[PDB]
Amino acid sequence: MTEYKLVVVGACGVGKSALTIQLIQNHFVDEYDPTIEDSYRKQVVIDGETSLLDILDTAGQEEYSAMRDQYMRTGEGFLLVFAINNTKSFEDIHHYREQIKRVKDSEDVPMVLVGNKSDLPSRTVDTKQAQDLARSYGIPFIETSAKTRQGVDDAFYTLVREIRKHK
Ligand SMILES: *CCC(=O)N1CCN(c2nc(OC[C@@H]3CCCN3C)nc3c2CCN(c2cccc4ccccc24)C3)CC1
Ligand SMILES: Nc1nc2c(ncn2[C@@H]2O[C@H](COP(=O)(O)OP(=O)(O)O)[C@@H](O)[C@H]2O)c(=O)[nH]1
Ligand SMILES: [Mg+2]
């Protein structure tokens, strides 16, 4: 059975853990421990294909040991996550995409831009700002809520479709 190694990246507080746990365990977590970095497995079906998803929810501390490089490099696709009510988190996306390109030593790595917390009023990042960042990377943009499940399957599934295209 085909396995997909997906890595969820982005600033603290954007909902990497809440999206990963909504997908895998179908509930919404308040203030998940930001020190906990885990891998989560899920049998799913995308375009009629029963696949195994191996999903790394990144956490802890920013650090660049060989060992961290090697654990991130196992990633076949990346969710670049920001929160639509957090402009600083959107302005950090470029950093995560640069570190992805470095450890994969490639200008073409399957990625999806995810604008999370779309159930919230008082958005500070507009749809157009995030569609233009994603068009600048040649990658898709999907709007999610870890809380209502809006777009959650579609963000993960769209990343899988990106990895298939790369093959
Ligand atoms: C709140 C806890 C949490 O979820 N995380 C801690 C911060 N983590 C993290 N943060 C950054 O950068 C923070 C900002 C952005 C610009 C400079 N800095 C002030 N960068 C990374 C991480 C996780 C580890 N990262 C990393 C290490 C090695 C290789 C790669 C390759 C590809 C992507 C990331 C890599 C970078 C994580 C979340
Ligand atoms: N309303 C709402 N809150 C969210 C969403 N995603 C995450 N949160 C909350 O935002 C906070 C940070 O999310 P968390 O999953 O810890 O993000 P992480 O640090 O990137 O893993 C927690 O209190 C979450 O419950 C969302 O889509 N909508
Ligand atoms: Mg977390």
Image (cartoon, rainbow, N blue to C red):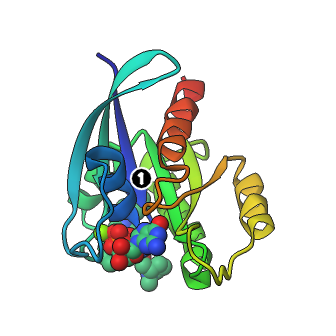
Does residue 6 sit above or below 145 in this rendering? above
Quadrant where the C terminus sits is: top right
Numbered circles on residues, count: 1
Q: Residue furthest front?
A: 148
Q: Is mark 1 within 8 Å of ligand 1?
A: yes
Q: As drawn, is 56 to the left or to the right of 161? A: left
The structure residue drawn at horizontal position 36% and vertical position 47%, both measured from the top left corner, is 23
Could you say whether the residue bearing mark 1 is in a helix, strand or loop? Answer: helix
Residue 10 can be seen, yes or no:
yes
Residue 21 or residue 88, whichever sits in front: 21
Horizontal relation, residue 96 to residue 57: left or right: right
Figure quadrant of residue 88: bottom right
Image location of residue 62, percent across then percent down: 32, 76
Residue at the image position 55 percent from the left and 47 percent from the top: 111
Q: Which residue is mark 1?
A: 103
Decide if residue 91 is on the left or right side of residue 155. right
| Residue type marked 1 | Val
State the residue at coordinates (53%, 25%).
164
Where does the N terminus fall, quadrant-wise?
top left
The residue drawn where x is 20% and y is 56% is 38
Q: Is residue 22 above or below residue 163?
A: below
Q: Position of residue 129 (x, y in %)?
A: 77, 69
Q: Is residue 14 visible?
A: no
How packed mark 1 is, by other alpha carbons closer than 10 Å (few <14, some 14-19, many 20 or more), is: some
Residue 115: x, y in percent?
59, 63
